[PDB]
Amino acid sequence: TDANRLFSYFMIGSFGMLSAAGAKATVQDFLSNMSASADVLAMAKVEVKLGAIPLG
Amino acid sequence: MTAAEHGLHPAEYPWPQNGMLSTFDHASLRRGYQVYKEVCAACHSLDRIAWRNLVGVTHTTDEAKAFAEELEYDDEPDDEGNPRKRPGKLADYIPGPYPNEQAARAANQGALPPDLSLIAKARHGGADYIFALLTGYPDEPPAGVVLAPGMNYNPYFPGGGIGMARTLFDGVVEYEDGTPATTSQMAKDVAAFLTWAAEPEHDERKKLGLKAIIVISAMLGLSVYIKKFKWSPIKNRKFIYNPP
Amino acid sequence: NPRKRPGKLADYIPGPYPNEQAARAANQGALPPDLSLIAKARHGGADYIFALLTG
Amino acid sequence: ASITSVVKTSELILKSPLLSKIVVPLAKTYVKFSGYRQLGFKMNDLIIEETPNMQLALRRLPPTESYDRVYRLIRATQFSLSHKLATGNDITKPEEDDHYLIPYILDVEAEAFEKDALDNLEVV
Amino acid sequence: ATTFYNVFVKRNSAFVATILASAFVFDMTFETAIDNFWDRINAGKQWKDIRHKY
Amino acid sequence: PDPAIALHEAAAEGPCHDFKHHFDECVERVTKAQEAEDYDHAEYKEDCVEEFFHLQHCINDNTADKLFRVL
Amino acid sequence: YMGWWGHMGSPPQKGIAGYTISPFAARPFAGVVHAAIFNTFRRTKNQALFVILPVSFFYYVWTQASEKNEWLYTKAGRHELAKAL
Amino acid sequence: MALRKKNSLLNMANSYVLDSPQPSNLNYFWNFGSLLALCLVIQLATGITLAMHYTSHASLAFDSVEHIMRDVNFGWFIRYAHANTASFFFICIYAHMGRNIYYGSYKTPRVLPWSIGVIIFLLLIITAFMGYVLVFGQMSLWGATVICNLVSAIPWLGEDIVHFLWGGFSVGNPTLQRFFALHYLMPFVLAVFALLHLIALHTAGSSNPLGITSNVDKLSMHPYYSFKDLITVFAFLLMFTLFVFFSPDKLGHPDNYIPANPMVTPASIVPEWYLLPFYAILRAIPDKLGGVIAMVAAILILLILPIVDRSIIRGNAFKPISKLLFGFFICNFLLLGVLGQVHIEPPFIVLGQICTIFYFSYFLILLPMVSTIENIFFYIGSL
Ligand code: HEC
Ligand code: HEM
Ligand code: HEM
Ligand SMILES: CCCCCC[C@H]1C(=O)O[C@H](C)[C@H](NC(=O)c2cccc(NC=O)c2O)C(=O)O[C@@H](C)[C@@H]1OC(=O)CC(C)C
Ligand SMILES: CCCCCCCCCCCCO[C@@H]1O[C@H](CO)[C@@H](O[C@H]2O[C@H](CO)[C@@H](O)[C@H](O)[C@H]2O)[C@H](O)[C@H]1O
């Protein structure tokens, strides 16, 4: 029966699905190490006051 | 070795964060920061933590910037190349009480108070050791112990004689949340805080591990079905031998 | 407290200025480069230094 | 080790009445605990064959004996991978555990050892 | 059920497309589900639970 | 007032009473030995660290969970 | 010593008929409950001594050694420690 | 002819991972080879990633590792994955060697894969030792100090060699920089040797748990062993997950989270757990040089198993006495491990000496005796 084959491909496909979801998670999390680290993200975005600054 | 030489091993306390699914109690973390700031920071540095690290853990961005802006840090030189100070920013590290080791030891009868950023990972026992140590100064040293001058008896510290005196007494801190600041409460809070300092990813790490455990368990179950499925022709094989 | 000592052979030859800003302030904005590599850091090498100082 | 060595030493033991009295019962128990018969092997099926000498002895087996050996190895491999043991007729009975290969390998080795001796002969 | 097989499984291109689309959906929903679960078992503990005081 | 003070006292009088007695006996002996003259010029000076550890280790085992429950 | 498919280096085979069924025709988990219980019990019982004997012996050794060591570094064990050094 | 067979490059992959003929009856202990391949891949991925964030200067090394833990996105994971996988690599390598000893994989015709394997084992020890130094915590420093001072026992030139390896008169920045470079390199050498021992094995093919020929009944490596290998990959990753995410410091020593201090000596310099048996062997010999030789001999003595095993039968499946002897050998190897982490005190000093003698006497006395006797029992017992 088609039912019979379909079941085993549902198992194979579930396994492929979790492997794909797991690989995406693994790659995305692992490669994010290469994005700017927390110290860099804070070395940027510099904040400055304006109250100190006189006209001219 | 004698148990004295090893130090008494600390009890296993049920910390909120013990447990595969448990985060830190962030209200305790905040209380613990207040203990660090009002008691420990007199002698101990927390050099690996920046003001930005408290944000969204213990403090809002505004509270943390306020803490940073109260301090002065070394700026780049002015136009005549003279040194300058600036107010602190979120990316600054929490500054130490002493400029160098020599200053630290001179203030502490020769002993050097370690940096506390990693102390929870750098001692067997972790939070339990910190909690046990801070709460474990007996009123009287066991009869027959000879303490060196400037040493205090504490059984959890290896050798028994520690250069750090008892520091937590009921009501040395006034918590902002109305929690009674008992010796034990303050030690629990500060020990939680220091554990967070040593492992700030702890909450995120355990959530991702929950996801990993679930997916990897499912994939393990499925991999066993698939293995059995593909191997069934070999396992089920039958032979008939007719000698020629 | 900080302290000074007399120099030893392993010490590096000390500069006239503590930082770039001090250097530029003393030289009408220009920064005199470090001369340790200047002969390799310019096309020409010794010839460039000789030509410049005499030119 | 050489099969020759094993066979010679065994013969020394079987000769000595004292020795045989104590060793033969032990060896029978050992073989029962060894449990190769429970996979339908004969003892000789277990001898290491990836040696030039043993390859030659296997080529000298009579066709019948050789075909039966291949069946026992394939059967045992199947029981191994199934984690089942032989049952019924598949279990090797003590009377069926014949040394079918020992004569062949002893002849192969006899020649190989003679060859080594004779390579070292000195005319007097 | 034959229909299901014929559409999603028979062609490998369709099967792999189905697997990847499923992976996308699983990934998104599982993230959301774990987030909610984690917040319930760690209730009153996390920064989001105490932030309102400030 | 510190919850630990009362829990430790309760555990000493109760489940760790045998260990409390040992430590007490030890301190009595050592103090008495220190009282006697030419103690400073003795080979072996006895402490009570061992007995102290046995007591503390016991108290901690009976108290740990109770203490953290009231914080 | 090993060839390849077609000439693997088997003695010539003859007279063995091999039969199997498709993975799709089989129950992959047929008799799994029986095997998980009875087969694993059989296989574990057969190998138990080879694990239990060495583990129990070396655990006993360790236990005696660690208990002696502990006792030597007590007050009671002062004298025996002095002799042992 | 199929492309996978026709094309020379594809054919090499084919011959190793797809059409490779395997015995049909390999059990789960044959899966450690692929787990060791997985460990080696995880160590390369995590290792190369850490190298992108690590600074090899001694003034900055420890701080760079804290930067990884605290600032780099997922840095905690990459660091703990790398550190824990080094432990798992040794669990899998001891398992793989144990499997090879129990099933007689070292016998003809597989002496060459075995012998290259013993070298892989040495490279792994060196690799993991150098990596441990890179943190430049207290265990890093005091580990490099004591281990490199063993070389001082080499007569005449020993001191000179130590100073040459350190690049100075003590462990310091030069040592750290050179261990970084070598720790990066050594895993690639280890991968090449891993590949060589497989090429060597290809001539005979895998042994099997019965110790008989498998030439009669072969199975393609794929799909059967491919899918079998996934079960242990996921089992491994479950174990990995429990350590990496839930207990990342269980296998380690807290002393390495204290920055290196040449003045302060730690309470106890004990190596990483997987080195402990060799450390116990070294302590057992009172002589400094004796100890070092014994420690190296404890690894190199594996090279004589092909000689000292006199059995006419390959492996222990059918040898009850050999199985008992092997059980005692393995448990003794674990006891040596435990004795490597106790203090040098009675009664562990004498016990360590007894266990060390037992370790060597297995190869030199017992295995030759037991294997000879079992030969005779098989022959007499089956008459
Ligand atoms: C005025 C001094 C002082 C105060 C206040 C102080 N410490 Fe210390 N601390 C020390 C000194 C000195 C040492 C080192 C003692 C030694 O090595 O003998 C030390 C050591 C420690 C150690 C490590 C002990 C070890 O195992 O090496 C920890 C943890 C610690 N302190 C935490 C704290 C915490 C938490 C507080 C307060 C909430 C605190 N300290 C308050 C001076 C202080
Ligand atoms: C067999 C492969 C490897 C093994 C067994 C191994 C082992 C180790 C070990 C034990 C440490 C100490 C870990 C710690 O406690 O923090 C470490 C650190 C390190 N390894 Fe590896 N390593 C391997 C491969 C590599 C490779 C290929 C690189 C590539 C550069 C690398 C880079 C590093 C770096 C940068 C560190 C220091 C950062 C740190 O301690 O995390 N490793 N390694
Ligand atoms: C990086 C480390 C190693 C890797 C990746 C590795 C990988 C493998 C693989 C994949 C196989 C074939 C599959 C298997 O039998 O498990 C194998 C077989 C083998 N390995 Fe290893 N191995 C490594 C280290 C070692 C060591 C240290 C030794 C010996 C001390 C060793 C000796 C062998 C032997 C003798 C075989 C043949 C065993 C047989 O099939 O009967 N290997 N190895
Ligand atoms: C892609 C072709 C390049 C050839 C080398 C690549 C790898 C390769 O051959 O993979 C195979 C999948 C191999 N497994 C086996 O031999 C194997 C054989 C029999 C049974 C089982 N298990 C039981 O159930 C097996 O696991 C394996 O894991 O060995 C790696 C180590 C190899 O890596 C290298 O040497 C290169 C480098 C990365 C170390
Ligand atoms: C062969 C590879 C091919 C090229 C593929 C390129 C992939 C590189 C993509 C890096 C993407 C990272 O992007 C970022 O991912 C992290 C997780 O890593 C997510 O972060 C989210 O989950 C993580 C844990 O997983 C938490 O720490 C975080 O609080 C949360 O926001 C971000 O929501 C997303 O902004």
Image (spheres, rainbow, N blue to C red):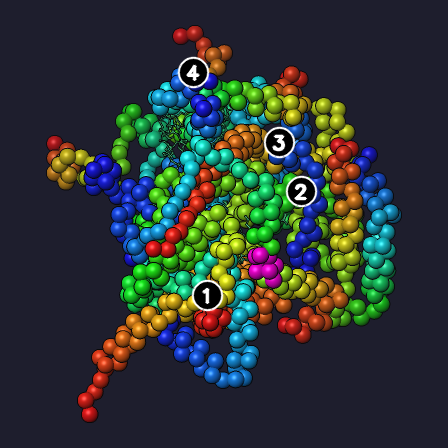
Q: Are marks 2 and 1 on the same chain?
A: no
Chain designation of label 2: B
- Say which residue label 4 marks: E3
Mark on residue D97? 1
- Mark 4–mark 2 CB contact (< 8 Å): no
In the image, H236 versus B178, the foreground residue is: H236
Amino acid type of the residue tagged 3 in the rendering: Leu
Instruction: Based on the picture, tell me whether residue B91 belongs to the magenta stretch.
Output: no
- Mark 4–mark 1 CB contact (< 8 Å): no
In the image, B11 versus D36, the foreground residue is: D36
In what element is the residue under mark 1?
loop
Instruction: Based on the picture, tell me whether residue G51 belongs to the magenta stretch.
Output: yes
Tell me what residue is drawn at x 85 percent, y 67 percent: F36
Spatial CA span between label 4 and label 1: 59 Å
Spatial CA span between label 4 and label 3: 43 Å
In the image, F21 versus H14, the foreground residue is: H14
- Say which residue label 3 marks: B21
Chain designation of label 3: B
Amino acid type of the residue tagged 4 in the rendering: Thr
Q: Are marks 4 and 1 on the same chain?
A: no
Q: Are marks 4 and 3 on the same chain?
A: no
- Foreground mark, 3 or 2? 3
Name the side, left or right, on which B205 lies relative to D74.
right
**For residue A46, which quarter of the picture?**
top left
Residue H382: x, y in percent? 47, 69
Quadrant of image for the N terminus of chain H: top left
| Above or below: residue H306 compared with residue H141 | below
Q: Earlier in the sequence, mark 3 or mark 2?
A: 3
Q: Main secondary structure of the magenta part?
A: helix
Amino acid type of the residue tagged 2 in the rendering: Asp
- Foreground mark, 2 or 1? 1
Name the side, left or right, on which H62 lies relative to H17.
right
